[PDB]
Image (cartoon, rainbow over all chains, first blue to last red; front, side):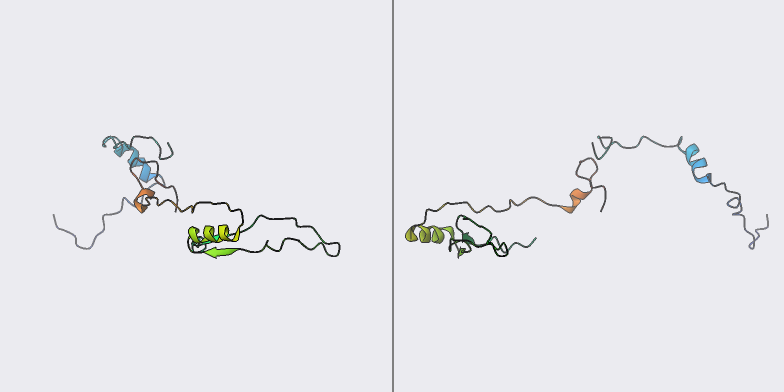
Length: 45
Length: 87
């Protein structure tokens, strides 16, 4: 209950693996939407 | 990329024999009217000069660049092939 005005809780960022970015980006991939289509699959096609 | 050299009508004559002299292999020639080029504002003046002088003349029309539609927005696109890949 007592709000501690002199503490830090952004500590989970300490124990982050070198892949942590993509480690949860891959999980976040599920909660997405179809990307809009530009027609040709490449700008060179 | 400079342009102000194709804004005049120049007349020049057929090239003739160019042999090498025995001494240093120079470029001795015989026709005096070889390094002779005449300028004219419009081709009508040039052709009038040619006929009145009496030289058999040949005519080539003034080729000019076609104006092409150019836009920087073509360097990028959503679907067009014209999108660039590097700047």
